[PDB]
Length: 165
Length: 11
Image (cartoon, rainbow over all chains, first blue to last red; front, side, top):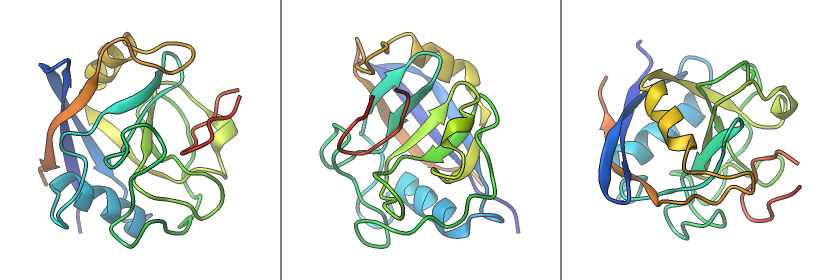
């Protein structure tokens, strides 16, 4: 099998910034990887296209995936509103880790974050399911619009997304 | 603190 590769084209107040592509570890977390892949192609009728990164904290991570409320309180999986913590085999070892945001054990929906640093304190609590394959420089450019409190100075959106491989 | 939650963002 081959792990899926997904992309996001990021825009900053509608201006295109660039493409970030992600390898999803379907061989290790199939259900979590499948959820993010299907939400990136929009094939169930809902997904990430047009949604924003609502909380970016420089040196920590960029968070997005709330396509229903756009503020951290909504979004849902392709399995129903929430699904279980599949496993915690993988850790938040450094910049580029793609991991699920949540509100406690077994509350995975659509929200995710992209780590810009090693965040070992989230190991065992947030399921790591992918990594940035190309476009880490686009993630870095994105951090310049966040703040310590997480609010962005510009609206950072996923102008388009889908699967490459 | 530095968490990534959905709904109540904690310190």
